[PDB]
Image (cartoon, coloured by chain):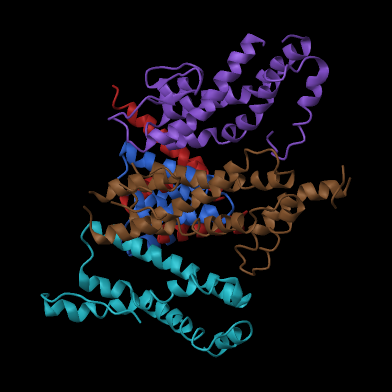
């Protein structure tokens, strides 16, 4: 109806602002990957643990390239 | 009187506009733990007046020279930024408290400490004699001040190096 | 199942292909699930401003303050500390 | 050298622990007065940069008090829990409150303020 | 009240912002809804509106005659263009988030507040000394060697 379309707008905003904080900080993330890391952080997950993973899978994708 | 109400008035005393009224900003009840922190915070706004009066009293008369303008027009680029900080602080008041302000405004308690004491050391100096009294503030060593004043000197000494690349004259 | 989508986004592969990495991701995430530090969005905010100021980018440090309020304005996010703690690390 | 007063009518099971937290405040009221004074030019180009680098730690001590009040609203901050949180601050603000009282005892400026930092986690 | 002000800064006075033929734009008196401390910053903000009104009134009046006076006003609107354009923007920012106060609106003017004052006496010297003819191309030039970069 309406309250189901007002929520899809307030999420496209926040997902557009977090993409600005992401580029001025020069994280290699992009709009597709960043939506995965946000969902995870909503359920409650150690960002000291989740960031060690991303700092590793990006560190192994080079040995294969 | 709620703590939030104090956070509402302080964001104005940072500019000159007055519970907190106008040399200390005597506040006039509330608990002693609140009045003390307001007093120091309110006084930072008072400094902003002393630096505003100079860039307004001398922006009036047309007999201040060509150097006294590049100085009075370089105390404004160091004030728009102080107006950007007040912008950000106001958007969060809709959370921040007194003890949270002290860390936010601990640095602009120094830049508003050098500028408010740089306009008193050079009061009656016009022309090059002013570009020689804002250079006697560089022999300080403090890496935060010597890298601020050594920028205002790079603007004030631009008109002087404009005559030179082109000394009291007699009509 | 959601951890396996991540390993397929970062590494471009299918879940039948990449299974050594996903074996390493269950090792780290698991046994480290519970949050270890007290959660507050205030402290994490004053560290993303302190970081964008340190890069002479003082204009984006006051834009974040306007984007962090909108997150509270809408109200579809339960844990706002976590997602910021992560975006700051990357 | 600051002295404090607590309460005539308070639980003894508190006052003995209050006097265990204050030595980080009294050791702080002597650092913030060292900054606002030894910043005067008539003290050399060393007693200045010593007061500047001694200010960044005061900034990080003000953040540690902010994160406690925001954690105090949820009530998760018991008095016993406080005595453990400030321990990194009770050791640092105990070092600086000893230099700021040993640089002003014997008037030092210039090299003699750079020797004391070489004899003194 | 925001959209009310952004018109008062455009040249349209109303009940909240009365107009006086001698002094200039100013707030009428205390208002209960708003705080009693803002009654100052607005008065500091109107010191800018008075300039634009006294500008556009002179621009329209064309007053003295001569092409060099016609062209001066013709050009005087060009320098005054970024003022208008920067004012249209304020409404857009307020249309987005409804948490912006007068503080931010006052902050946005910034450059216009330190420009109009220095470009106000240039007009006053003309209307007070009957500067007729090409002599304008010096009276404006003698003030072109000012220190203020914006001017």
Residue C34 in sight: no
Q: Residue furthest front?
A: B171
Q: Residue at x 34, y 61 (%)?
A: D67
Residue B77 higher or lower than D110, as above or below: above
> Chain A shown in which color?
red
Q: Residue at x 61, y 29 (%)?
A: E116
The quadrant the N terminus of chain D occupies is bottom left
Q: Quadrant of residue B62?
A: top right
Query: Is residue E94 positioned above or below E149 on the image?
Result: above
Left or right: A24 in relation to E142: left
In the displayed structure image, the side of residue B7 where residue A16 appears, left or right: right
Across and down, in percent, residue E136 comes to 78, 20
Please tell me in which quadrant of the rendered image residue A47 appears.
Answer: bottom left
Q: Position of residue B9 (x, y in %)?
A: 35, 45
User: Which residue occupies 49% across, 42% down?
Assistant: A19
Q: Which chain is purple?
A: E
What colour do you see for chain D? Answer: cyan
Where's residue C34, x and y in %?
Answer: 30, 61
Tell me the brown chain: B
Q: Give how far across and how far down residue E44 sits, in percent.
A: 48, 34
* Most foreground residue, B154 or E125: E125
- Name the one closer to the observer, A18 or B74: B74
Q: Is residue A33 above or below residue B135?
A: above
Tell me, yes or no, if residue E103 can be seen here: yes
**Colour in which the image shows chain C:** blue
Number of marks: 0
């Amino acid at each position: 109806a309406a309250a189901a379309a007002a929520n899809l707008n307030a999420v496209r905003e926040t997902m557009d602002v977090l993409l600005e904080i992401s580029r001025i900080l020069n994280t290699g993330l992009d709009m597709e990957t960043l939506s995965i890391c946000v969902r995870l952080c909503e359920q409650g997950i150690n960002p000291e643990a989740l960031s060690s993973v991303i700092k590793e899978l990006r560190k192994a994708t080079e040995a294969l390239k | 009187i709620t703590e939030a109400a104090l956070v509402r008035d302080i964001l104005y005393v940072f500019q000159g506009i007055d519970n907190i009224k106008m040399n200390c900003y005597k506040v006039e009840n509330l608990s002693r733990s609140l009045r003390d922190t307001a007093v120091r915070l309110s006084e930072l706004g008072w400094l902003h007046n002393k630096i505003r009066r100079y860039t307004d009293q001398r922006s009036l008369d047309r007999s201040f020279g060509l150097v006294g303008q590049s100085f009075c027009a370089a105390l404004h680029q160091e004030l728009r930024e102080y107006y950007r900080l007040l912008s950000v602080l106001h958007s969060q008041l809709q959370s921040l408290t007194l003890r949270r302000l002290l860390v936010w405004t601990y640095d602009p308690k120094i830049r508003l400490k050098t500028l408010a004491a740089l306009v008193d050391h050079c009061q009656g100096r016009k022309g090059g004699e002013l570009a020689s009294a804002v250079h006697a503030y560089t022999k300080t060593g403090d890496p935060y001040m010597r890298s601020l004043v050594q920028h205002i000197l790079s603007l004030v000494s631009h008109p002087v190096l404009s005559f030179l690349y082109r000394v009291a004259s007699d009509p | 199942v959601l951890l396996q989508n991540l390993c397929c986004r970062i590494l471009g592969r299918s879940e039948a292909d990449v299974a050594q990495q996903f074996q390493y991701a269950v090792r780290v995430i698991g046994s480290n699930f519970a949050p270890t530090v007290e959660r507050d969005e205030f402290l994490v905010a004053e560290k993303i401003k302190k970081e964008l100021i340190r890069q002479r980018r003082e204009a984006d440090a006051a834009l974040f303050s306007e984007l962090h309020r909108k997150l509270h304005s809408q109200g579809v996010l339960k844990n706002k500390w976590s997602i910021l703690y992560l975006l700051l690390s990357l | 050298s600051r002295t404090f007063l607590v309460d005539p009518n308070l639980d003894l099971s508190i006052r003995e622990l209050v006097h265990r937290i204050l030595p980080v405040a009294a050791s702080y009221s002597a650092v913030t007065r060292f900054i606002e004074e030894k910043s005067s030019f008539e003290y050399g180009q060393v007693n200045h940069a010593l007061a500047a680098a001694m200010r960044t730690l005061v900034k990080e001590h003000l953040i540690l008090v902010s994160q406690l009040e925001q954690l105090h609203r949820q009530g998760l901050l018991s008095l016993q829990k406080l005595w453990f949180y400030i321990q990194p601050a009770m050791r640092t603000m105990d070092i600086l409150a000893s230099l700021a009282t040993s640089v002003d005892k014997g008037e030092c400026l210039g090299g003699s303020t750079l020797s004391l930092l070489h004899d003194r986690q | 009240m925001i959209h009310e002000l952004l018109l008062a800064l455009s040249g349209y006075p109303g009940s909240i912002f009365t107009w006086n033929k001698r002094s200039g734009l100013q707030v009428s008196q205390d208002f209960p809804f708003l705080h009693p401390s803002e009654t100052s910053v607005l008065n500091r903000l109107c010191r800018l509106g008075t300039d634009y009104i006294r500008f556009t009134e002179f621009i329209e009046q064309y007053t003295l005659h001569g092409i060099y006076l016609r062209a001066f006003c013709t050009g005087l609107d060009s320098v005054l263009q970024p003022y208008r354009q920067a004012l249209l923007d304020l409404e857009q920012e307020f249309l987005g988030d409804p948490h912006l106060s007068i503080s931010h609106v006052n902050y946005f003017l910034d450059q216009f507040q330190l420009l109009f004052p220095s470009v106000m006496v240039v007009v006053e010297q003309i209307k007070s000394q009957k500067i007729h003819g090409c002599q304008i191309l010096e009276t404006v030039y003698k003030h072109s060697c000012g220190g203020l970069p914006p001017v």
